[PDB]
Image (cartoon, rainbow over the protein chains, first blue to last red):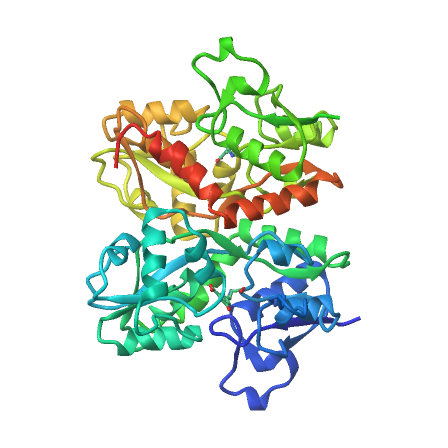
Length: 258
Length: 260
Ligand SMILES: O=C(O)c1cc(O)cc([C@H]2CCN[C@@H]2C(=O)O)c1
Ligand SMILES: O=C(O)c1cc(O)cc([C@H]2CCN[C@@H]2C(=O)O)c1
């Protein structure tokens, strides 16, 4: 049976080729996760169809209805067989699906517009002139809410009370906010996205400071899936053989623009 | 039955306390992995016994005999229930035991004597006056042997043919060699150990450059063990709650001897 892969349209993980109207099926798309899906399938010996997650979401359980959205939802309700995407390995997700070991590492990080006199989280925490914030909901916002670290706690109390709101609706809005705010806004987002944008025109942003936490992206299959074991071994082999590092370099830097 | 934990005496992971003689059982020991064991056990609801791996090894399969040694071996052959140690998640190990998601990230990194004019692997590869090497067997050596990366290929060829030998038998030997070599020896080792040593007296070494690869330490259980599921969930909760970062900072930096 053909394996149904769910993934998400987000550069540079999955894009539609410029000539996509000339192509069919899996060949319409390109990117990091497109290449990885190919390697995973080759190493596990399956045929697959790439599909884009219906609701454009990653995977969250609605606190009221208990329903899972996004790619995780597509796995647990049987719409797809495997998710290959920048999907963070988290406890609540691990409880309902299986994750491979991580294929990429990342953490919360600071994006500034080039020129901004900020080099770290401590720098942000001790001032208020350069506003800074996060997505208006999600794990990053929650990281700050629950932090007991002095710097991060100070950043959190600043963010919640700051006027006007320092929170944004989408990461795209956050990046745009940095870019148009004339050095007066910094945005807190995944290091992977931060590092990618730094290599996109007009090359006006920069990742600064170390990551504030650590996590990884993992390939997700449903509990008891016949694919889980082989997929996991595949990730480790690709890492050990240098392929994941080669793939990140390809999509972030060789194809960079700055 | 009380869970049998196997681990290895390696600082700052597991250390005998200075007054260990006045103590008994698990209380004899301290370190990152001792703290981690307590938190894993707490969240999973089991009591445990910390035991030290009999043969002093991590886990490799002999090519000829095909026996697994070290902590992996103790799990594979049923001598221990769980391994909690700086044990790298690797493909060959993953095939014979179960691993939690990683509790610590790391990679191959360069240690220099403070003052050595070297910032990267590429720097090392382009010259010979500063000799450089690694453990004389194991994954870091094999990483270089098999690499297709031009720079690492060049370093492997250099290392294999360099005289006198640039390899060392142990980590301690490697560190001692860097420190006593007046800047003419650099040592390739795990970033985690590199970072630790930089915070130890006499504060005469430093980590330089990015890591050359990426991997993680994982909590290991025998394949199919009922402990695997809860232990993995525990690791994830501890990471997301900030505890793993807290333990790292505690043992590497709060207890560091070279200051901020
Ligand atoms: O850091 C956040 O606050 C955040 C909020 C979201 O709504 C989505 C994400 C995505 C981006 C890709 N990986 C995350 C994931 O897999 O869930 C991150
Ligand atoms: O970097 C090496 O080449 C290397 C060689 C070894 O013989 C042992 C180790 C240990 C140290 C802790 N983690 C590794 C592990 O889990 O195997 C590392």
